[PDB]
Image (cartoon, rainbow, N blue to C red):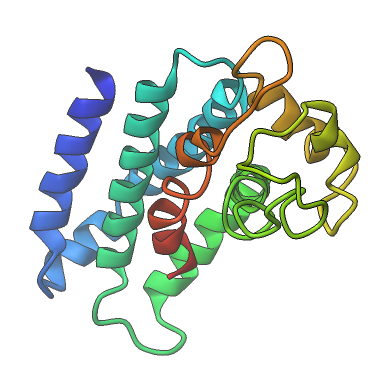
Length: 193
């Protein structure tokens, strides 16, 4: 419910400053919006890191990335009509440097799940050819990932912990459908923009 209310508020702010209004843009520039945005990215990064595990918080994660997309759309709507070395750009870069750790966290999360290093490596298919679908022998996943992905627990073992799925040894492409691939592509596209 809180995510839905925040989404509606962000949509209202966008429709306030979707068109070039200048006065409204300056009004929200000289306000407390930047602190709220910084806190929002902080809770986004930490909640994404905490909820990357488990298997019951998928819908909350979906609404979470949806609110992320809405805020990034709003932020892009701020930069409409900017020039080189604009004041809005200065406020923007101040906002980034005020929350550098959260930005690094969300970027690291986006790089691991989708945005290369996932659904691109195609583990054991182009590297081992398991004579079938992407069932994977569980231990084959750790036997894989000898690539550009880091060996840290937050990079290699992170995927293993997040992709527990079945009990004994079986995985599937449904893991790639649920985590990474379809999410974090459209959501991260606005961040890249």
